[PDB]
Length: 185
Ligand SMILES: C=CC[C@@H]1/C=C(\C)C[C@H](C)C[C@H](OC)[C@H]2O[C@@](O)(C(=O)C(=O)N3CCCC[C@H]3C(=O)O[C@H](/C(C)=C/[C@@H]3CC[C@@H](O)[C@H](OC)C3)[C@H](C)[C@@H](O)CC1=O)[C@H](C)C[C@@H]2OC
Image (cartoon, rainbow, N blue to C red; front, side):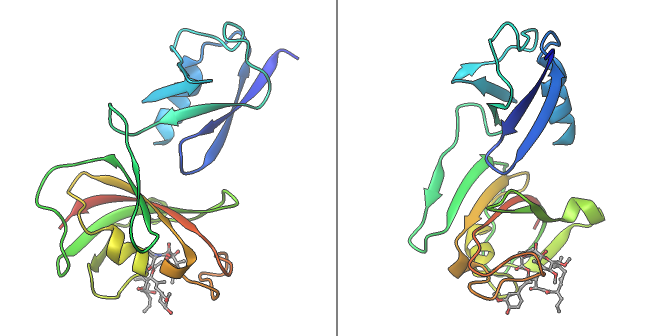
C-alpha cells in the first residue's frame, strides 16, 4: 500500500524498481545509473528530489530512461532492414571493413531476457570487421562507429540467425537487440 514498483525502459530492456511512495526518485535514478541521464514520466522530466507521491504515480507505471546524447537520438532503418541508434557518438576515425575492432556488448531478446554480455566474462570481444566472422547485422552495424561510441543494433532475423537460432536461447526467427561499445580499433 505504501510501496510502489516502477518499470524503467531504456530502449534495450525493462528493469523494475520498488520504492516507498515518499522516497525521492533520486534513489531509483542512482540505482539505475549504477547498473550502467534523463528520466521521463508521461513525457515530463523527473527531478531527483521528487517522490512518486508528488507525481501521482501508480504501481507498474513506466519511466523512460534516456541514456542517449543530450539533444536526442534517432533510430535509423537501413536498406537491409537493420536498425541502429547512436546513443553516444564517440570520436575518432570511423570503423571500416578490414579493421579489427574491440567491443563490449550486451544482447537481449524480444521477450526482454538478456542472453549474453561480454561484461559478464569481463572480456572484450574483438573481430575483423567486414569479414563474415559475425552475423550480418554486426558486419553492417559496427561499420561507422567511433571509439567511445555506444550503438544499439536492432537486428532482424535475416541479419541474425534466421530460422536456426543460436546459443540455445536465441529461438528461431528472433529479432536481436545488441548494445555495442567500441573500445578500440
Ligand atoms: C569457432 C567458434 C567459436 C567462436 C566463439 C567466440 C569467438 C566467442 C564469442 C564471444 C561468442 C560468444 O561465446 C560466448 C557467444 O555469443 C553469443 O552469445 C552472442 O551474443 C552473439 O550472437 N554474438 C557474439 C558477439 C558478436 C555477434 C554475435 C555473433 O555473430 O557471434 C558469432 C556467431 C555465433 C556466428 C554464427 C556462426 C555460425 C553461423 O552458422 C551463424 O550464421 C548465422 C553465425 C561468433 C562470434 C562466431 O563468429 C565465432 C564463434 O562462434 C552467441 C548467441 C553464442 C556465442 O557462443 C558460441
